[PDB]
Image (cartoon, rainbow over all chains, first blue to last red):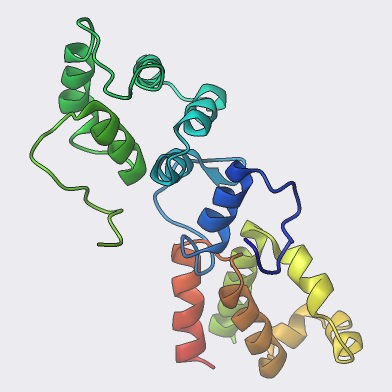
Length: 135
Length: 80
């Protein structure tokens, strides 16, 4: 971000810096393919990267604003965040896991899968298909 | 000719997707006068060099997203 552009149009907030990474950096040669995008922005990729950065809170906020419909997950994100990040509810974690296996596991947008898998610790057999790009 | 028109239109289909306007404003230089008075037929019976430069900018810059970008690179390779 600290190098030309726009200089990004908006304020230097962390969120925008990541939007820049996702948009300017190599998610697009000349933009496209299989993300879920609203208003020109891959939300799931954003949450994933923000999470990658360590900005969990911001990632949570993005989800809140998201316009999405897996919303139960939204709940499970927030408490994961609230606690020590080992979100352990004696309650639902089990429920989240079932949904992952049935709905999410066989399908979806790579980043969405990443967020579910990583936050949830959903499927211990380990690896994320499309978006592991670095060692 | 029909194929050529297809190609030009295809590029435009690409451009419509996004952030075309910003690049255009920044890019245009002395050549610009020639560019602005370019007709569709001019594209139909192409003015190759300018488009190549522009397309390169589309790819170099972030504007093209995903699959689109791959397509131009293919295009530059094929007919450029």
